[PDB]
Amino acid sequence: VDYKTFDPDLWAAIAKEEERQEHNLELIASENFVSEAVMAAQGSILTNKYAEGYPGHRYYGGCEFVDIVENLAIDRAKELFGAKFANVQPHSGSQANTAAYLALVEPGDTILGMDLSAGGHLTHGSPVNFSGKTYHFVAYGVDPTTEVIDYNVVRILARKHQPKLIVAGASAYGRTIDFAKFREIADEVGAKLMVDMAHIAGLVAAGLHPNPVPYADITTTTTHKTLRGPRGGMILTNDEALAKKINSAVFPGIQGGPLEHVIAGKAVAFKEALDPAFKEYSEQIIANAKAMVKVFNQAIGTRVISGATDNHLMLIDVRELGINGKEAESILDSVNITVNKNSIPFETLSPFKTSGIRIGTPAITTRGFKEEDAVKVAELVVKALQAKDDNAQLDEVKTGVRELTEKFPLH
Amino acid sequence: DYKTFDPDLWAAIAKEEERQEHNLELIASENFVSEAVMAAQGSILTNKYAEGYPGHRYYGGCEFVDIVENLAIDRAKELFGAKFANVQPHSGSQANTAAYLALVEPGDTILGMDLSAGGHLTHGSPVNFSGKTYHFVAYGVDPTTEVIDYNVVRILARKHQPKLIVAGASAYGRTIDFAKFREIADEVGAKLMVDMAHIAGLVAAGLHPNPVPYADITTTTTHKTLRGPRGGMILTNDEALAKKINSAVFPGIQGGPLEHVIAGKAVAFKEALDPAFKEYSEQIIANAKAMVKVFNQAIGTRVISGATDNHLMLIDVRELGINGKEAESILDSVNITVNKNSIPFETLSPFKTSGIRIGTPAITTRGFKEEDAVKVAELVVKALQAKDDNAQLDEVKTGVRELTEKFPLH
């Protein structure tokens, strides 16, 4: 705080955000709370070192010890996911995907990925994103009745459109993905396979989701979200030739100097995920999400997309309640519950008129929530959303949220 | 306490802190950030997803993240006099990537500084996204004075008719006149983009011409002479370009920003708005000029262009019978860190080059003054003149311990 008196405005804001995180029920599926060690690594003196290149092949001298750190992150990532090669330098998931495309396809090549309304990410073909501006994207959706992936539809589109690359992985799909089936379809049309496991990387590490590493030519991921690491990206592969193309695509391809203090935080998070406690944490993530799905299925006005969850998240249609995703998002904020609106299958992508919201449990699971507490959260969401013009009932939800946050403190 | 779980990681960081303590860091792109900057990067702000921009976020719960990001934006605008700022780029590379997207189309012709005479990798390297996506032509420095000839820039601009002209360098020790680049850009109908990453700290202190009133878009890193955390930033006075810049960063090429790093940016900008930072930046240039004087008068060292106006210098070492790579190895063995660097009109390959690059921002942050910066230059010459004579190299290794022990860092 000696260094904080110089800048009262900044640290007052950080102090208020810390209190906000304490009194808020975080339900955004991509959020989490990292350990003291992860934060301490990001605030280390490693931010002072320029380390362009790769361990043992740096352009600058004096990298003997940052090489140890980056190699710790690389080797722990290989142990975590069973990969033969790893690149821990991407600044984010978006940069990891950017370099992965460069190692696999050419500009204008055809790529078959998941439809953006059905679960795909903006980096999987959006025209306001680099991906949709650089490559020719075709999309597979989900079944109209069950709202799960139809792998025969994937095979049909792959044959008809002859993609050079098939992308699997999603940011808003709460069901199991059969990566081995994607590898079979790619082998048939002679395509490559890339998997973006950013949202489910923690569940993959705990063995609770099929592992894409043995099937994908290249696997990309974030280090945050379910992995509970610092904010950043990572690229994995088992192909020695692709590993060099990946290494060259990241630097000098699209980035310059890496963030070694973030990479130290990645190494800390990877060792935490190697501990048996992480499997117990990831199992509680799914158990909490399934309990919330039961409440939303039973409630009047909330429709769970596909009607179930196999992982950490769920999509909810609120059109039956006479509101859209933006209004529901605004309502839950007024009772200290944070979600995000999200497109749902078969909508024509209208990022502000969508009918859906997205909910995930990794954050509250880190705070210590169990199934009965997750049930109470889902019941509080329903109560606020059904509270059509009812300040007295919105206030009761605020009391319930306060009871939960004080029962499970953060720090 | 929390270190007990992972003793191997925290032992490696302790050795790196020890290496930084007893090493003389002369790499021109390095610096040492304050305790407040590191504490901001190590804050709980890493837990918040903040896609979008303040007041227009895609998610809820951003009331105080918007305050933090607006602090960085407003302090950057105050620091540099810009009407618009984007503080989300993860690095200088990403800031440059987004700047090209808001200015030109793939395949367009761009005129920038030659990579052998100062230009950065993101200024047209064929192994980089810049050289791969656009058609880059180069301007260099005069063969006699080894500085930029603005008539030659005018000549090459009329010949190629570029859509964009790039100013700024990574290994150029003289003042860059951004007002002359604007005139040349106006004459051929081209836009102007300035990459001030190496000199942004000197620009902030008012010790180098400010490109913001002249460039269509200004890009920079927040580290190096700015002494901020590792990251990037984009500035402009054009509102229409500011919207294209915002769209190019997100959802253009990035996703969620690093708001804990952005907090460190706001911390570093306030430290730069303090009068102590101007006196710091003045000491940078004074220390650099003192070293150049030692190298000019020494046998075996030739300062490129013969002087410096900023934080760095290039040193030709061929007269010693030495490569840049050879000189880098000699100095590394006595705990002095430089990097080999190509000199204007380089004869050999980048695998060996002909010179070394030296900068003072790091030792200046440790508290070195001119008298100490003269001793480091004397120790460099003595090591490079000692032809594998370990009796001399042991003496300079003793000398660098005197300096690092005299100026403690951590």
Image (cartoon, coloured by chain):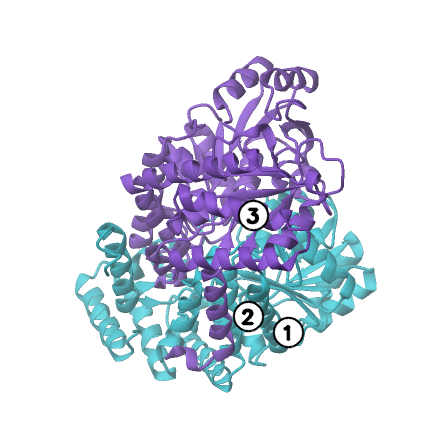
Chain colours: A cyan, B purple
Whether discs 1 and 3 lie on one chain: the answer is no
Farthest top residue in view: B187
Q: Quadrant of residue B238?
A: top left
In the depicted structure, whether residue B245 falls above or below residue A150:
above
Chain hosting mark 1: A
SS of the residue under disc 2: loop
User: Which mark is in front, 2 or 3?
Assistant: 3
SS of the residue under disc 3: helix
Label 1 – label 3 distance at C-alpha = 42 Å
Q: Quadrant of residue A369?
A: bottom left
Amino acid at the residue labelled 2: Ile
The mark that comes first in sequence, 2 or 1, is 1
Residue positioned 55% across, 80% down in the render: A206
Please tell me which residue lies in front, B368 or B360.
B368
Instruction: Name the mark on residue B380.
Output: 3
Asked if residue A275 shows in the view, the reply is: yes
Please tell me which residue lies in front, B55 or B279.
B279
Mark 3 surroundings within 10 Å by alpha-carbon count, few (fewer than 14), some (14 through 19), many (20 or more): many
Mark 1 surroundings within 10 Å by alpha-carbon count, few (fewer than 14), some (14 through 19), many (20 or more): some
Amino acid at the residue labelled 1: Lys
Whether discs 2 and 3 lie on one chain: the answer is no
Left or right: A242 as drawn, with respect to A63: right
Mark 2 surroundings within 10 Å by alpha-carbon count, few (fewer than 14), some (14 through 19), many (20 or more): many
Q: Position of residue B404 (x, y in %)?
A: 44, 57
Residue that carries the numbered disc 2 in the rendered image: A200
User: Which mark is in front, 2 or 1?
Assistant: 1
Q: Position of residue B187 (x, y in %)?
A: 57, 13
Amino acid at the residue labelled 3: Val
Please tell me which residue lies in front, B338 or B333.
B333
Instruction: Name the mark on residue A78.
Output: 1
SS of the residue under disc 1: helix
